[PDB]
Image (cartoon, rainbow, N blue to C red):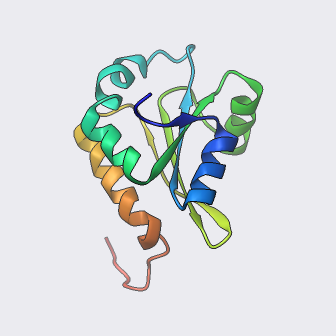
Amino acid sequence: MSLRWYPYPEALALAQAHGRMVMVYFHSEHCPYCQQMNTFVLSDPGVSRLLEARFVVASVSVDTPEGQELARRYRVPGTPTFVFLVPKAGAWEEVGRLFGSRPRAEFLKELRQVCVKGGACGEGHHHHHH
């Protein structure tokens, strides 16, 4: 495999033990909205390269108990649901969620933003009214 798609437990463990970031990818076959983007846009070598760099991707099935549970916990629809979690100090930080597939342009925007969010999340010192 090229990009690393591990189960939710492993993805968190790999990230935690290797100082990486977590990409929680919620997928369902009952939500066929992702299959269009996932195949081309998400499997894009450019996109995948940003994930390979610092991310551990969690392939979670929303229709099965663990995904069902996470759907209760995080409150998630079908697919594609991208939840980015950063391991910092000793806690997991959700830096945002992407839903609606989007073109890789917008996806890479957030994928790059999250790349910064890993250390930039927690900002608010420099207040802004926009």
Does residue 2 sit above or below 53 in this rendering? above
Q: Residue at x 37, y 31 (%)?
A: 101
Q: Residue at x 27, y 43 (%)?
A: 106
Image quarter of the C terminus: bottom left
Q: Is residue 122 left or right of residue 87?
A: left
Residue 69: x and y, percent?
75, 35
Q: Is residue 121 left or right of residue 69?
A: left
Residue 83: x and y, percent?
52, 45
**Of residues 42 and 18, which is closer to you in this image?**
18
Does residue 71 sit above or below 125 in this rendering? above
Residue 57: x and y, percent?
51, 40
Residue closest to the far left: 105
Image quarter of the N terminus: top left
Q: Is residue 103 visible?
A: no
Please tell me how many numbered marks the rendered image carries.
0
**Of residues 72 and 39, which is closer to you in this image?**
39
Q: Residue at x 39, y 45 (%)?
A: 51
| Res 40 → quadrant | top left
Q: Is residue 42 left or right of residue 103?
A: right
Q: Is residue 83 visible?
A: yes
